Image (cartoon, coloured by chain):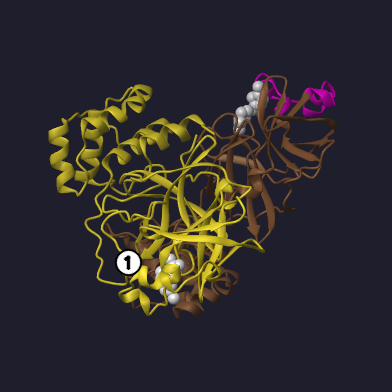
Chain colours: A yellow, B brown
Amino acid sequence: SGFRKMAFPSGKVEGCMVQVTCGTTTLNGLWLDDVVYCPRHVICTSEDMLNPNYEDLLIRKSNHNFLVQAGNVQLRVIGHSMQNCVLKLKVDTANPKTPKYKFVRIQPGQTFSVLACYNGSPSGVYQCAMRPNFTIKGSFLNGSCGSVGFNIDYDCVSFCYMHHMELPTGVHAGTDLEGNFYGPFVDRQTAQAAGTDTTITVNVLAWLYAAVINGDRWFLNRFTTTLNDFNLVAMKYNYEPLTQDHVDILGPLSAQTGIAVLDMCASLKELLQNGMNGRTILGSALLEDEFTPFDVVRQCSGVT
Amino acid sequence: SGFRKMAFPSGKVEGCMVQVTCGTTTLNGLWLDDVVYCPRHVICTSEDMLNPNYEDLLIRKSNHNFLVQAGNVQLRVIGHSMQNCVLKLKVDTANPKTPKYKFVRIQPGQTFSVLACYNGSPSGVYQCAMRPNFTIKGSFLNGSCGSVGFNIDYDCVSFCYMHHMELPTGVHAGTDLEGNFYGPFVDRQTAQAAGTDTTITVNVLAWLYAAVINGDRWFLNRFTTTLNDFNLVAMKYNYEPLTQDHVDILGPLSAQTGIAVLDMCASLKELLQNGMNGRTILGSALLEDEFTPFDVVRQCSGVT
Ligand SMILES: *CC(=O)N1CCN(Cc2ccc(Br)s2)CC1
Ligand SMILES: *CC(=O)N1CCN(Cc2ccc(Br)s2)CC1
């Protein structure tokens, strides 16, 4: 029993973290096979970051300008290229610790683990979600850029995030491993405001199921609702509209607890309308939305 | 910016996890040098667990009865002994992935990372605290026993916890790596009630400092208090008494933010007396008490 915000074990990703230095900017890179992936703003002077022309800035850089260090050993750079907002540095040595891996672009509402790194050294690991506004709520200081987000399916690491920037509101923007930003964000120091941070309804419902499975039940009521009725309440409280797709995904949690999805929706509706009246759910005083239905099943069934 | 509940990177501990089977009970073991550490209840039949005599049960076990598997490779057991509530299985091979390590017994209020494992395979990593009642609030299903808690100081893993049992109230009890239980708990299926789960005051204050450092400031007020006055409020709300020792430990966070510890105490006093009036602090609607002053400094300064 017990339900915790849980990150994937980070060992497989720890083995991929390196330090990348171009001029006097040091950040993190991801070493997979004979390629090191890092944010392209590694080539910038803070001066450059107001309106950088990355193609023009990169022309001034040679393979020998990219200093790549895996622990205390230097990697020899034999090629470099820009793909969207990331640099691919070809090195002469395949990373012997390369796990089985994929590059995936996640949808908003999907969760992943971040391995926060500084100078190619891991500091810690925490669980995040791609917000509906395409930001993440991370923990990233200067030097953390090039830290990556990932999911693990048994033996295969799916990399989904590379950290690139902090908005003035203290939230985080980055790319997939093809260097495409999540949302409308650019690697430029400019006016970039996040949109509405809407709540991930399907995740809150997943987490209500997790609560019931672990003995927190005070919020179950005698009520039911419809998708259309519930969605009127979701609109009012800046919750994502719930779809039949979301209901279908909650099917297994429904089946295990014997609580119909629309009944749990009615519980969530009362919680939205009435708040928690100073009570808690799985040690939280707000509705948690960074567990997916897949996350709740995984943790509740002890998958490795 | 941003502040997250952050676990240590788990790679160094992943390399130490094995599976231990005695008869038909499988749980996790910790392989360090040529010793595998595991809970002694691995020798029990669920029958035994009502009133087990571990010394008598162990006499029926031989080295060849302890099946120890590191991934898909079996370790040869050449010795076994009981130390308090753990078994030490001597194997013929030193773990080549043994990190630099220590065994430490933590005090209540200290935080650590758990690597949840099943059948010697890591499922995930989360951050815990030794509660003042000597329980932890974990995520542990059947098969998770022998999962370990740890801290990392640069290169040295300090193991502080091995998981042994769940109380009927859904909270967790275990041992240090010398096999001594935290608190009064025994490895017997009996009437074991946790005492008062008091709040770790010094940690809440550490986390209020972390909030100020990351721009959450609405809860700063015009007030101050004294240790004795604050402690009257802590008593009323089942908070640990704050000592000069705690004030001294908060010294660096005080110095960095320029908010005197007793002023932050007065903020905490108003929060206790008035609640958060539907507001949040670092994305929480309750007062977080599982960050130490050391944790806040580490995360706020990017230590690896
Ligand atoms: C995420 C992170 O580490 N940083 C620091 C770098 N910053 C952009 C810059 C790159 C080169 C220089 Br000089 S400034 C983004 C945030
Ligand atoms: C923490 C954990 O995995 N478990 C399962 C084992 N249980 C005690 C027992 C050991 C042998 C048998 Br059969 S039952 C404690 C909780």
Whether label 1 lies within 8 Å of ligand 1 gets the answer no
Q: Chain of mark 1?
A: A
Residue B277: image quadrant is: bottom left
In the displayed structure, does residue B294 sit left or right of residue B72? left
What percent of the width, then of the height, locates residue B140? 54, 36
Callout 1 amino acid = Leu
Taking the image as shown, residue B41 lies to the left or right of residue A219, namely: right
Above or below for A40 versus B238: below
x, y percent for residue B127: 53, 50
> Does residue B303 appear in the picture of this structure?
yes
| B207 displayed left or right of B251 | left
Magenta segment:
B42-65
Quadrant showing the C terminus of chain A: top right
Q: Which residue is mark 1?
A: A167
**Of A61 and B202, the residue lying toward us:** A61
Numbered disc 1: secondary structure: loop
